[PDB]
Image (cartoon, rainbow, N blue to C red):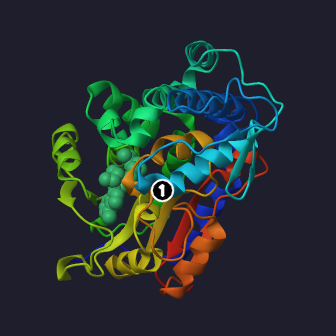
Amino acid sequence: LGGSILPKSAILDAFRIAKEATDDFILNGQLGTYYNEVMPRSTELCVAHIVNAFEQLGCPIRSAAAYQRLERVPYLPKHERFMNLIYGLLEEARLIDINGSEITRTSVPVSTKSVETMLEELLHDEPLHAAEHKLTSLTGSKFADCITGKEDGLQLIFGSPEGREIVTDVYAKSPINAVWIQQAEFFLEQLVKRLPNTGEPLRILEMGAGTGGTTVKMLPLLERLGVPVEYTMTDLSSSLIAAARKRFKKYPFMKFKVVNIESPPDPQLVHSQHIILATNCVHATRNLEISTRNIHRILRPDGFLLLLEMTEQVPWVDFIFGLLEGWWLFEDGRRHALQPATHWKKILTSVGYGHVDWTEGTRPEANIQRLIIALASEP
Ligand SMILES: Nc1ncnc2c1ncn2[C@@H]1O[C@H](CSCC[C@H](N)C(=O)O)[C@@H](O)[C@H]1O
């Protein structure tokens, strides 16, 4: 299996070009008001949903006087870490003061706008970011039921077609994700222009491909570039793969396979791939050292990992995904699944990657997610 030549300069020069355009991708992709104008509104909607759930669970937070002691709401033990984050959000919104175990009400009034009016206005005002706001209310309106076990967050999202459509749109269409996928397209296109042509394929493996939020852009891109390629789309979920096998049959350069990031690679995967793509999946594993070491062993020596990772917490993301067991699997010293790029570099370097870089910019959104590239060998 002779694969393409992949000079280090092609990677580093393409990444530098993409990196310097980060703020351009944020503006073009309609994310340039997200941190300062959209996120306070989605955070407000989360908080309102929380207040409603608390009232439903017997906490009179809406009517409580200043300094009133509030009892903790009921919830399943598995939600302890999440609910500490939830109470944190209420404190950041200045509705409560926390003092260790003691929760007390502030003088700040709860908003009088309903969550229905909040959503309606946000959907009308910010239609490009609709998907995550709809998802926020899908679980948010059932928040008391979820944290007590009467409903399950994973079932709510994926058990209905409406939820499945929203979450696909979140991963593919919402600027908060599409910006950096589009930037990865630019990186890869500039990369391929710098490759020798030997007739041999570029071998690309996507981990955690899930709903195909990245995949749906990569395949037309590789189709249009027309250089030999084998694209292996993988995920832990066999249903998501089976669906993708149908959806993406159009493309003849495709392989589809169930692959667990946490598993040691079978011999057939060892040193096989030029590029591993991984969008917001590696953080969901138990141990980042183990996962990134596994990924390293699947890379050819001339290859690299391209992470697309959320590097800063966003309240609506925690509010929704924090309901899911998959958000709390870390057991490697992290206190949250998501980590800043500096931590990712620490892990990546410690398991043998030779060069780590990431996107940055002056816009605040450039800190929310990053492309993080990690070369298997040191240049
Ligand atoms: N151990 C593991 N190995 C592989 N994929 C995993 C995994 N743990 C979680 N995942 C997958 O990682 C994805 C995280 S969702 C992030 C969005 C995703 N790339 C998309 O476009 O849909 C999900 O598809 C989930 O099934």
Q: Residue at left 39%, top 29%? A: 166
* Residue 145 lies in quadrant: top left
Disc 1, SS: helix
- Figure label count: 1
Q: Is residue 205 visible?
A: no
| Residue 61 x, y percent position in the rendering | 66, 30
Q: State the residue at coordinates (35%, 49%).
A: 222
Q: Position of residue 83 (x, y in %)?
A: 54, 49
Structural crowding at the residue carrying mark 1, measured as other residues with C-alpha within 10 Å and reported as few (<14), some (14–19) or many (≥20):
many
Amino acid on which disc 1 is placed: Leu
Camera-nearest residue between 108 and 343 = 108
Q: Quadrant of residue 24?
A: top right
Residue of label 1: 188
Q: Residue at x 64, y 16 (%)?
A: 125
Quarter of the figure with the C terminus: bottom right
Question: Is 6 on the left-hand or right-hand side of 241?
Answer: right
Seen in the picture, residue 207 relative to 374 is either above or below; the reply is: above
Against 19, is 48 above or below? above
Q: Which of the pair 39/231 is nearer the observer?
A: 39
Question: Who is closer to the viewer here, 86 or 67?
Answer: 67
Q: From the viewer's perspective, tell me whether residue 40 is left or right of residue 165.
A: right
